[PDB]
View (cartoon, rainbow, N blue to C red):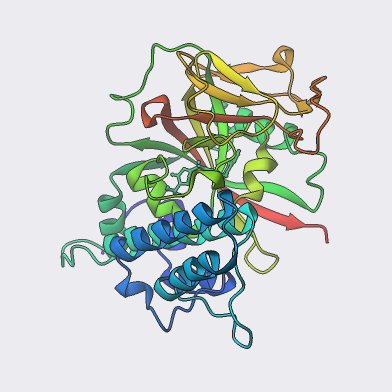
Length: 351
Ligand SMILES: CCC(CC)N1CCN(C(=O)c2cc(Cn3c(=O)[nH]c(=O)c4ccccc43)ccc2F)CC1=O
């Protein structure tokens, strides 16, 4: 009938596509036929998180053996995987837990997406306008010659990590973001307000937009989060772009630039999942990397420090294989976040 800007319809179309959701889950080896995503419940997702913590309990307590296999057997029962020919493998490292956490994470935002897309069937509203309404989050496109588009494009290209050399990033569209209740709840008076990157999977963008960026649930095992249950940001565009998991086939992603009020940072050299306890007054955790932009080449876009620049070495040591190659910012309270811009990104793979 009558809708909205053609670039926003293309955004709503991309993120409300459940067919692509049904595929991303099979690439994570989730049996979508045994448990259709339509009949997804927060109770089953909670139950899977609990079983992951059970699995963690056996790992951290050295109780391998059967107690581990009994927990994986429970998790694999309530969260149906599809490896086809072989027995589903055990989960014996934090990498496997942190991978199952993403499955559950994505499986959570798919519940939110299907719930939202299954909402009002109003005859006086084109379907892409109902979804946009149920999002409760403004998405207004910016001119390609606008002040914001120019600095954000430089932010993307100037902070593409040298070690992420398999793709190039091309800004297809820039939307201004405003989630209802985010400005009014923001710690707008805290210092070190920075425009940082965050990237996630496609299925999660109805979640992050309608519900904001969120603290991990209580039922999740804390060993899957290298710095605690917080909202993770990067100052390197490609570091967040990697987390979009853009495919050679599906080479489109969404990057989010948010205002992050960090305040005083509790800078850590090596990951520590109990990092929130080490705050003790400080307002954020800064994962120190060996390569990052420099304070000289920074600018300020509409109130916030934009960490521009080519980026170089930081002098950061702790001789150990977990020396972050690039910096990592964590906040443990959604009030320190204000979603501000959204980028439609085209990944041009080079291999
Ligand atoms: C519970 C709801 C779901 C909804 C999707 N969720 C997930 C948790 N979460 C995070 O921020 C989070 C992200 C990562 C990985 N990581 C990423 O993915 N993108 C990035 O740019 C990024 C940049 C630097 C470092 C890590 C990054 C790890 C742990 C986290 F806690 C907020 C949230 O709301």
